[PDB]
Image (cartoon, rainbow, N blue to C red):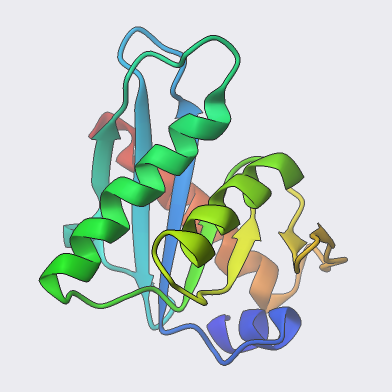
Amino acid sequence: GSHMLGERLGIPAPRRIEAFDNSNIYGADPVSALVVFLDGKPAKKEYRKYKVKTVAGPNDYETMREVVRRRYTRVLKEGLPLPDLIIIDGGKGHLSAVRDVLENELGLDVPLAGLSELLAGDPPDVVPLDRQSQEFYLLQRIQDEVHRFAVM
């Protein structure tokens, strides 16, 4: 499905996809979940739970910026494999906030997409995917893994 997903996004098939889920940043234990898919398959040993600071008021934009900064500054320092595609959960505002960090702080030109509705491009807009397409199934498998990872 990565081949079709890349084609839909106008990027080469992403061999490494990293997805961030911030559904739990408001709970008693604020956390951002990261799942990694390599060659379209789960890379479970690379999943990470990023505990974040209590969201400052309604500003969850800085919370996501901080999580992206946190992971990738480390990845860049250690020379670890960079993603070919980053997926985040949140709207246009969250994509704008993350893209700014990626381009201006990390100097990365990594494809970025939002979250079911898929937002892509800069400025972003909805990509009309079919619910039974291979690319949609891949995105759904990624979301399912985020859910199973919940216990962790």
